[PDB]
Image (cartoon, rainbow over all chains, first blue to last red; front, side):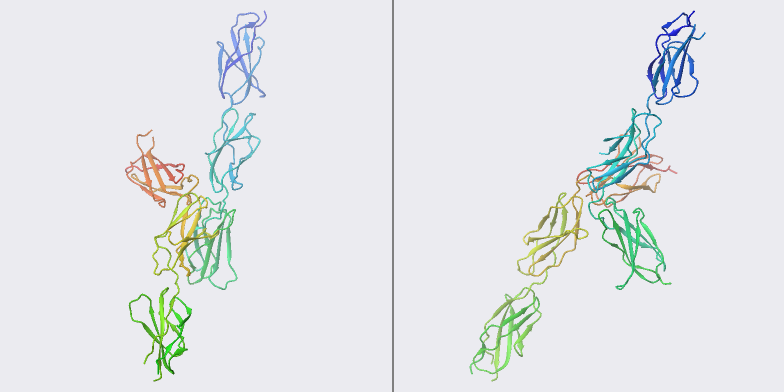
Length: 282
Length: 291
């Protein structure tokens, strides 16, 4: 009595990202009936492990608890003991959405050009991928790239850009990245110049700058009041987010001339001078 | 003894706006000398009043206390050593102009992305010189200065050929041959060519059960003329409220009359000549309970 063995490989009916629905194609078989038990054997390809299995009452079965984008192999055994496995079916599960690229940075390269960069990407699957970049009013860049040049923009403009990673699935959008093109003109001077916490040795100085002019740096020049002074002091603040400063080491009962500048890709601003800093006796 | 009278008119040799230097031209004369005293008579033309007079010891006198751009007439009388003779020929001269004050009601207003219009009240000067208006356009750093002269019968000058979203300093003065006083600088922005950035630095503080204080920052230079604060109860909704602020210098706002223990969706917009900005959202408006 020849042990029965299916004619056709199992058929995949519906595939998800975590589940596969299979028609095991038990019948028709070759050999002698009747059949008292049908077994579907399944296993992720290139995984060194024993085959998993379940008994199938009928013809249709759903494999749950699967992994994304994984290829699985399927075959069926029938019992009249156990016979030879039928033809093998291979299928791959579905892609899930990828999170946006890491270390996203949008930076000015010119007055008409922004550069968007991200960290190199290592997916959990061998999907072919590209990055979709959206300027918020679309350009598709090959996934082997980590930088995209956004051209033909206008000087002194503010742009918002987001990205996502596309395979077959569509990716999760990044949060917007806001950046400015470089300025075409000199920056405006610092504003709201107040001086507080005067001592005999020190004083606090604060200001605000206007956004939109690519102000990358701030110079605070101070100097003892005289028509005859051989020395002045330039403090150079290369991070234009700092908006206050403690002046220390001054001379008591002394009048100072304080000037505050702001610079960008074009040049410096006019002096935002302050009405006199005069330290206290002692 | 035929009474002595000068033959030439006095000569004006220097001229200011408040003074005149005169050679009285006493000699040569007609008649019989010698000369005991010389007298220069002078008067503002078209002034119904008596002639003023000054004694001149020698030949050169300096008339002070004069008025700007005023026509005067001069003549000289002589006394001999042994009364007063005929006045000599008359010399007319006009004093010099002083610098006029700047135009009044000065106003600089943006008309387009590339045009500013400068206006002023019609000018009625204290003299009758042919005058003009000089308009000086500079940048904030006083870079590309452009001077334009406009005929004095005009009250408006269009300063086109500029650039969108830029600031310009404009001052004016009224000139004759005497240069006028420069007016105070007027600064104005050209109209935007693009939509305004959304307001930023949005802060919601002083939360109560009834209110809150919304602060924000907008960017100068985009010709932003209005601010819209739109808030609804978080939920579709059958109603919402639009606070409309026409003074774009207001950066705070006190929302009042708010239901206790409730969540609001607050959006803030910026409006200019091109249109409206993207909304500046905040889900952060959640009041405190009646307690």
